[PDB]
Length: 13
Image (cartoon, rainbow, N blue to C red; front, side, top):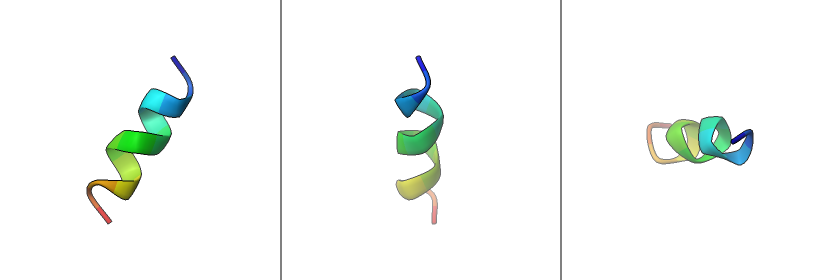
């Protein structure tokens, strides 16, 4: 999914 990349980002920084 796209938000998956967004969630993997937020969670990181």
